[PDB]
Length: 237
Image (tube, rainbow, N blue to C red; front, side):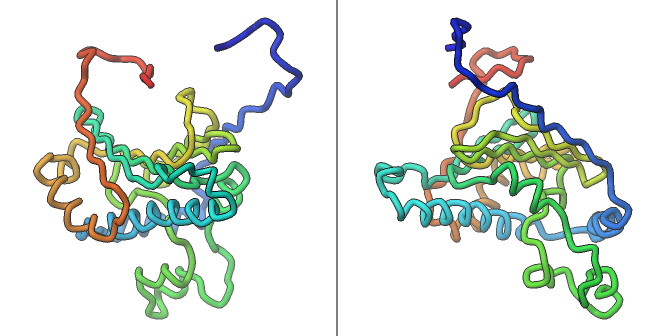
């Protein structure tokens, strides 16, 4: 309840809204990822879901200091909400998420010549699968999407809305209007030409095979539109 009846002493805060265009060196690497077509959509779940479970394991481990913080768990679950018209598959975890300082700090890659650089290594006989132990875990979700948007908030830190569409140009903006309790809201903007990742029949089958590694509750939601006509950003808790 917004009480204008004299709140408290507090800073006006600054809007962390930074927009950046492709960096020449990173544009080389990232565009080559676009050049390198991916004919296997299975790796998508395998490595991305790995991060989802990891984000939960980290929060699960951190809570060993105080089990009372978890009450009895409840935070160990993966919720999937697919938007049929919006073509937006929303996967939200209740894990640790990411922090404000860490987001902008870990945001980058190795462009410096530290013995092994993917550019030179490419001609020296490297491989895409070298990333695992050579640098970077999850850059983003642009391997086969229109745009990748992650709204995360550590329950103590602020919420941010990170989005990137194949790297061309991205923007990092804090506070998305919609409140966040904790976790990571990973919403894939799928193109209409990417119906391969949205057909009800396909969703069940593809997510069935790769959900084996998921030991946490798998909840595929079927959220139907009640209001019928909606054109605002108003959510309902």
